[PDB]
């Protein structure tokens, strides 16, 4: 009716719009986290099935230069590209929905001093603190090796340094779960709150 | 509650639907590949049992004109029709679930210069690249002769050209496994990625 | 309070109403696009399941004369009517929510020179530019053959000209994805902006 | 924000709810059809195993008065009750999930003029047209005798009239498959669309 | 537009939010009930396979003091801890999702006066009336001994009193199914409505 009433109504509308902004961000985070869990499981199964005849898993080759089309034709030994070309998953499933990069996959050792990639690790980079903790709470207890680093979008620092050591001792801040003694730690609320401490985080998941 | 929120929710729903599209296609491919492996094994056993007294295997007769009912009554020498009529196979198992054609079966020679079909070959046509590579990874190491061609649905180019030469040398692109020297090649991920290079592929499997 | 104040208030109210008009149109578009994606996937699965025993897919018969009731009783060989009568989907799911026509379904060839409908194609007509690009960005990468034409509501020009050639070369303007060499193009934002250039557009989706 | 926007949103929500209604009905139909296929196969195997020493199969006794508890103690010669008491079936497996009745089982003759139940037939009543055609497309080709009638829920008209004549000539409307000459008809889409023409249908499956 | 319209819209929004609260509670209940059914079956199979060489099942030891990590290392004879350590199930599968306690497992006698645990029983405590009736209607007919008690979260009163008597007579209020005469009662809706009469309920399932 009056201008003051219109001003109050417009303020209420703006408040509702801001709430919508927050809710949309949370919904995007939830969808991407669920997709990441599903796609990491798919990659785990596909890698286990695809490289059984080799007896070892391929070394890390950076997928950061791959495009939406080049992943289907690249033949430089990138593990996720090989999985896509084998028909085990689509390029959309191979792409980290949060960072926008294709999921980095490298080798991992299951014994001290070993030089053979008897296991494999994959890295999800560019995760926010909320996404990091959500992924942990959802799927961390289901993987044998879980580590938290600070790799940003476009980087795979955990895999670019060599094969992931699955036998490293846990310290409930960086290495959460591993094959080391007393390394099968259940990720409760307190343990999750003790990690993913940065605004930009990454998660390395390794299996044998 | 607002129209913008509804639009965001509808976008999320559409994304889920597209994911369902991809998953349904993959499930169909997996089911058809498993059925093809099982049915090719059944055909192999049935062929070996049915023609033991003849001492040779029948020449290729095109099954591309057979219907769901004519396969049970045809008497023109089509091998898969004979197997169905002998009770070793139902028409459903005799049909390539991917191409929709009845599986083509022809003779094959186990020595250089031979004119007697001492072995038999079967062709699976109309395969996609993913289906081709999945079938290879599943079952290729279990057959003595494995070849990859480009026969589309409704065609059996590998069998229509005469008896399959099981002694042909392997080249890791077309002839993957054979009875030739150094022809017993294990199909690794690296090898499988070097073949089934077209969008339409066929697999010829031959046994003694 | 005064007449000028109420005039200003009424102007603000009219602005809000115009915004509501825009938002309602966008919500309708989003709902129809999501429904189209879902129903096209359902029809694809239903066609794959229903015609397996035939070994080929039915030729195009125009569904443009069907009504809400006649689709359940028509027996002239219309593919979508057969799918509805088989219980695979309801008449509402069989109807294009944008153009109001029942979805046109025809045969498609998966090889050069073939006269057998070894695949099937479906046409969505009467799409606006926004709807065309939204459907592409949502689901285009999940279909083996994707083409963009200008068929208006009440017309199926892409299917009425014969079987759809799934091997046609892509040109990023009309044929976006196909089974031809280099035809597996990912639909990015730029590629989507390069197509659906008319105010009235149609999308042909073909599968094996 | 405004009441008109709320009205539009509520309309969209109602449309989604109606779609959910349709999808829930379809999911229930699919689950019941799969359960019926599985349970009919289980009953077939159980009947073949249980009555081998008798040399003939029991005459039809109506199971329509059986309850969830009386099936485990009834001793009036009802075949499904005998199968349940023998441990081959559970009462849930013996119940038609669509009509709610226990599956009717009667004798069947495998020759003209015979008075001995050398085969057995089972009836599924109360099927809708969609359920009838789905069951046919799923399992019809796997049974030697398949007939379509109009027995409603709570009735077994096909079995209450005496032993099922497995040698009756097929007519692609009521008797689809039988042991008669030219009675081994494959059930394609057209043939399925030619039967189950009522809103209430029943299916009789008979085996030797 | 006006403040009154905003108030009406906010009331509608609050009503929708309350409906969402109810729906979220129901979804959580359904998920937990399905998980409980699955995990109880897994535990039943694991007990049947793990203790075959012993000839008897272990006595009840309270798992209420176990933590997320101590279940993997406890060696005090707790049955669910032994099953977890044997690799039969994960700690998450061993935990009652409703009460938050690890599932209590104890011995059970299959004859009058027996002092040997020839069967095993498991207790699900802290169930609401809705959850109790849902679990019954889902799985009660599939277990040989089903009893309803009032054990709250953190208590296992049924198992802490000694071995469960599987031969106890049924009374349709506390003992629903057992090995006693006339103890194989089917759980219909009317019989389910006569049990789980408290706000806090527990279900004891015992098998041979």
Image: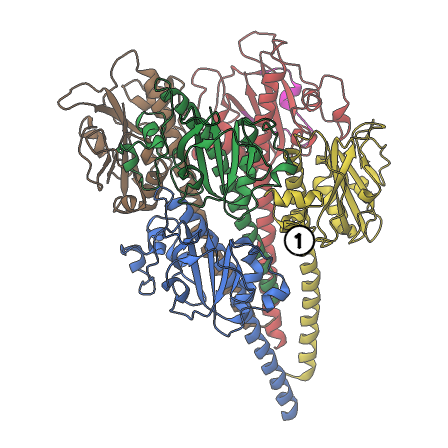
Chain colours: A yellow, B green, C blue, D brown, E red
Q: Give me the residue at 68% from left, 34% from top.
A: E100
B153 lies above or below E80: below
Q: Position of residue B144 (x, y in %)?
A: 52, 27
Identify the magenta region.
Answer: E147-164
Count the labels in the image.
1
Q: Which quarter of the picture shows residue E19?
A: bottom right
Residue C2 visible in this rendered orientation of the protein: no
Q: Give me the residue at 30% from left, 28% from top.
A: B85
Q: Is residue E148 magenta?
A: yes
Q: Position of residue E66 (x, y in %)?
A: 75, 27
- Residue in front for this viewpoint, B177 or E9: B177
The extreme front residue here reads B113
B121 lies above or below D190: above
Q: Secondary structure at mark 1?
A: helix
Mark 1 belongs to which subunit?
A
Residue B179 visible in this rendered orientation of the protein: yes
How many neighbours does mark 1 have within 10 angstroms: few (below 14), some (14-19), or many (20 or more)? some
Q: Which quarter of the picture shows residue A77?
A: top right
Q: Is residue D34 magenta?
A: no
- Locate residue B22 relative to residue C125 in the image: left or right: right
- Residue in front for this viewpoint, C19 or A96: A96
- Per the image, the residue denoted by label 1 is A70
A14 lies above or below A166: below
- Locate residue A35 relative to residue A200 in the image: left or right: left
- Residue in front for this viewpoint, B10 or B168: B168
Q: Give me the residue at 70% from left, 59% from top.
A: A25
The N terminus of chain C appears in which quarter of the rendering?
Answer: bottom right
- Locate residue A106 relative to residue D121 in the image: left or right: right
The extreme bottom residue here reads C3
Q: Position of residue D66 (x, y in %)?
A: 32, 27
- Residue in front for this viewpoint, B174 or A74: B174
Q: Position of residue B78 (x, y in %)?
A: 33, 33
């Amino acid at each position: 009716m009056s201008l003051l009433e219109v001003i109050i109504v417009l303020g209420i509308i703006g408040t509702i719009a801001a709430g919508v902004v927050i809710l949309a961000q949370r919904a995007f985070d939830s969808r991407t986290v669920s997709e990441l869990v599903t796609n990491t499981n798919t990659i785990r199964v596909a890698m286990k099935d695809a490289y059984q005849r080799d007896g070892k898993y391929p070394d890390y080759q950076a997928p950061l230069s791959l495009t939406a089309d080049s992943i289907k034709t690249d033949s430089t030994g990138i593990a996720v590209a090989q999985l896509v070309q084998l028909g085990k998953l689509t390029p959309d499933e191979a792409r980290n929905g949060i960072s926008g990069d294709y999921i980095g996959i490298g080798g991992a050792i299951t014994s001290s001093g070993s030089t053979i990639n008897k296991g494999f690790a994959m890295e999800l980079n560019g995760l926010s603190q909320e996404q990091c903790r959500s992924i942990l709470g959802q799927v961390g207890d289901n993987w044998e090796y879980v580590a938290v680093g600070t790799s940003p979008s476009g980087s795979y620092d955990a895999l670019s340094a060599g094969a992931v050591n699955m036998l490293a001792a846990t310290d409930n801040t960086t290495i959460l779960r591993s094959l080391a003694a007393n390394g099968q730690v259940s990720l409760t609320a307190e343990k999750i709150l003790k990690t993913c401490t940065a605004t930009v985080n990454s998660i390395t998941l390794a299996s044998r």
